[PDB]
Image (cartoon, rainbow, N blue to C red; front, side):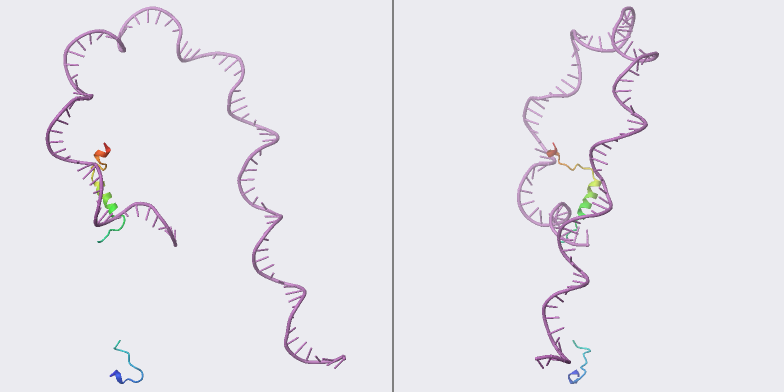
Length: 46
DNA sequence: TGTCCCCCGCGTTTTAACCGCCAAGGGGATTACTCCCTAGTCTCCAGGCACGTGTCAGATATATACATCCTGTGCATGTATTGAACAGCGACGAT
């Protein structure tokens, strides 16, 4: 085999999930623009 | 384009909003009654407006002084360049 190669040795063969900032904000925009429920609390306002 | 930081998102902790139910009296709604106040009417006239007029406060034209806005000189200083005056090394002749 290559153990007998004395010159010109043949070397061929051997060796949680986070959302991006701004996404939840936009989703909140979509959520409250569809609804009409009051946003400010009732008792602190009173 | 480049930096630094100011919110965004998310888990955990803290608070009071919200609902359900009862208890109570403050005040608004409603009625009945009376009279004081305002619409309506008439007569009377001066307060308010049109019209006319007279003139001075203000617009216009023209001359001058004040302000300012910007560019072009100067200055000054640093730097670059160049000339000159120190410095070889060696061959020669005079001593």
